[PDB]
Length: 173
Image (cartoon, rainbow, N blue to C red; front, side, top):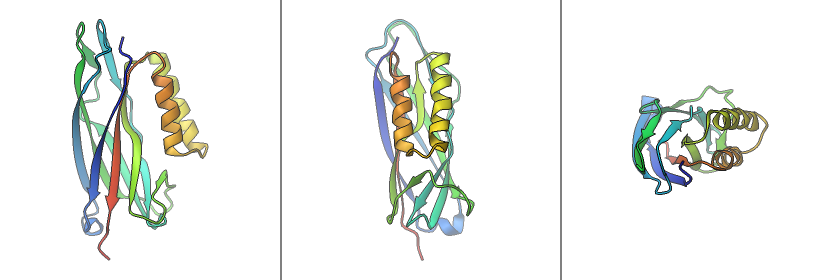
């Protein structure tokens, strides 16, 4: 079993001339160490969801598409505590009718918890956390509230390893 709730945060600066390139990609890699892991363990990357980010009173809407660098389970040997994970995010313009998931209000930066999450929890727990998350999101609650609820569900008697992201965009105009 593993039991820790661990996170890491990175910064993504959307370049000022994104409006001309209309795409940008970043890749992040982190080595987690959960010293509570005992015996052998399987760490599962949860399928991520695209996130629509609204900036400048949602007049700029960006589609964030997340993908695991490796989607396969991570297996830890007996009393192994460390593992490497990571993801790429691709930022593209969102469709004009896209519903904003995370909003910067008047500004150009947002903080997003849990853009990509791994868990040592069981299939049952992860499956039900995943469906409740998407439901919670459609239900109107904030991304943060939904991801917190999911993390707490995954972390009950298991480990959770989260990537968080700060995105900022100061467009040329």
